[PDB]
Amino acid sequence: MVVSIIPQFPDIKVSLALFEQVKNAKEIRSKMSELSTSFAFIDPRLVCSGEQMYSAIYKTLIEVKYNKMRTRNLNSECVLCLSPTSNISDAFLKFGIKDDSSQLICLKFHTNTDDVDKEQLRTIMTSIVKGQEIEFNDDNLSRFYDEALIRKIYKLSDDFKPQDVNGLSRALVDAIQ
């Protein structure tokens, strides 16, 4: 897993873990709203890069710090900011894990943590998720995204013709920012 801190928001830490060969996506999805106070579970088919996720996390803390929290918690707020929609139920429907998900991103905002307990967190995540943790990095995210779904959901122009994941990513960061 990765623990990420934005310089201009020094008291917030976000942990990101990536899981593959996930077996219990259905069970997790059924408890998604209840689980949101502890984790967001995001469908990697919609996420092509780390910078996409970091851009969403930044946008989240900006909206919350310099505006208003629209949802019940930061984990959910981040899913809302990752998505083009203004409605959280729509964001969960599109970006949350699906019954048929075989990979997932597990995200958690820590506000009160002075120093994240990485072994405890990993233990809890793996108690909830039945799958194999792999590194949260661009090499792995590049494997699991679905350009078609991404194009449709972020409303990318058919004219828009990226040459690689870097180009696609850059356009998503733009949509998000």
Image (cartoon, rainbow, N blue to C red):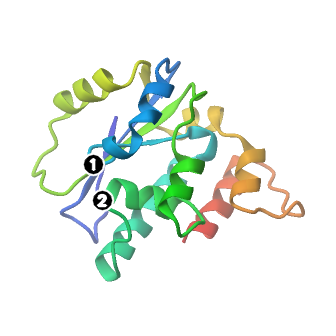
Q: Secondary structure at mark 1?
A: loop
Count the marks: how many?
A: 2
Q: Is residue 69 above or below residue 79?
A: below
Image quadrant holding the C terminus, namely bottom right
Q: Disc 2 marks which residue?
A: 73
Along the polypeptide, which appears first: circle 1 or circle 2?
1
Determine the CA span between mark 1 and mark 2.
6 Å
Could you tell me if residue 132 is visible in this image?
yes
| Residue 71 image offset from top left, x and y in percent | 37, 65
Residue furthest right in the image: 159
| Quadrant in which residue 59 is drawn | bottom left
Residue at 84 percent of width and 62 percent of height: 160
Horizontal arrangement in the rendering, residue 74 relative to residue 156 (left or right): left
Q: Which mark is residue 52?
A: none
Horizontal arrangement in the rendering, residue 112 relative to residue 29 (left or right): left
Residue furthest bottom in the image: 66
Which residue is at the front of the view, 114 or 78?
78
| Quadrant in which residue 131 is drawn | top left
Residue at 43 percent of width and 18 percent of height: 132
Could you tell me if residue 51 is visible in this image?
no
| Residue 23 image offset from top left, x and y in percent | 49, 17
Horizontal arrangement in the rendering, residue 121 relative to residue 34 (left or right): left
Q: Secondary structure at mark 2?
A: loop
Q: Are marks 1 and 2 in contact (CB under 8 Å)?
A: yes
Q: Amino acid at mark 2?
A: Asn
Q: Disc 1 marks which residue?
A: 37
Q: Is residue 87 above or below residue 153?
A: below
